[PDB]
Image (cartoon, rainbow, N blue to C red; front, side, top):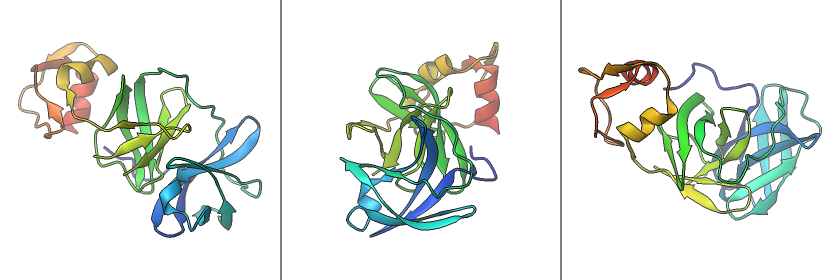
Length: 192
């Protein structure tokens, strides 16, 4: 459940501890987002492809955002996702992009969520928050939702493809197996 390569806008973030982050163009400005607890006060060394620099961050709860105008790399356009948004989401971790879903008052990732500071973005490219603390997603307001197990039938709601028997596919403990029929794309993802 992880791409081979991290996205080009994924960064390492090192302050008082070890984290990662992401770079986006938000209201016309290039910003870096990460987890506030990894900073040395509000400062960290941020590094990625073609970039290595100290940044100072605006902190709200465990959410942190910095202007980074010297960033010359990939900085996809993003706005914060709409309040109440639910759907498929993506964790941008230092070792690759990992799928999951955001539902009402919870998140679920198919794998571990990366370092603290991993951006969580929606299927339309909007920023949900960053992974902190298996774990929590902290939104730009500093409020959070916990990563929780999910019923297999609920997870199905986020996937397409005709219903197929789940058959012998093994599913981890963070999926509550309450059905044995699932949309084909979810079956295929789980079996990969």
